[PDB]
Image (cartoon, rainbow, N blue to C red; front, top):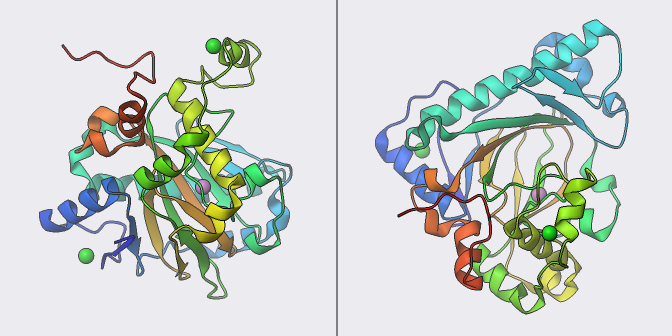
Length: 297
Ligand SMILES: [Cl-]
Ligand SMILES: [Cl-]
Ligand SMILES: [Co+2]
């Protein structure tokens, strides 16, 4: 069940335990949780931001709720205040929603960056490794996770009713198996140099190295991109969805105007840690893939 539909229509929805169970089981099994009726409304004063010309550089519009800092956009202080306010509201509403839906995770949910994406997807064109029309799990060369989960909340806020078109691929374990013969260890000392030179934020663990290989090699495997099991789904305007993007194979084909919120979660906070990419990779390679891993006696 690649997509599990939910009826919640409010950011302050209280959930029954049955729905909470359905959500955590689905999320950890690598399903997308879909909320067709959960819209994120904009203030009148924010409507001007539904315009791609606000993106100023190569990086997209982002906000760090921990530090209250806005990046990737230039303009008048009052306009940056309004834009920061929009993104902050998204961070607050998504964080509250996740705490209402996933009490099992308790305080282990750690918010990361909020993003606003006003550029139309279908007009994009970049390197194959960065081409997100190719199925992938998320792995960022400059930002290793140390094994922690990448959990993302998405809202389509297109004001013309346009959907956001995704494809959702096969389960992570099948993707890993498919690419296994192509995986290789890192060159000795290279990850240490990436750290020393500031190319990576922190040290790229072996896990991060392998997730990156999956990401990159999977995107270059043209036969796999064309023929692997995948379902195309249009997320309607006014909907929200939640996904572990490091586990769910996905691609983005078209759409415009999206809010996105990233959270991190340690593997030991999961209900079923054995389903995580870290544990699946450690089992497949029979080794510890993060050196800072906690030790269980
Ligand atoms: Cl429901
Ligand atoms: Cl190294
Ligand atoms: Co992605």
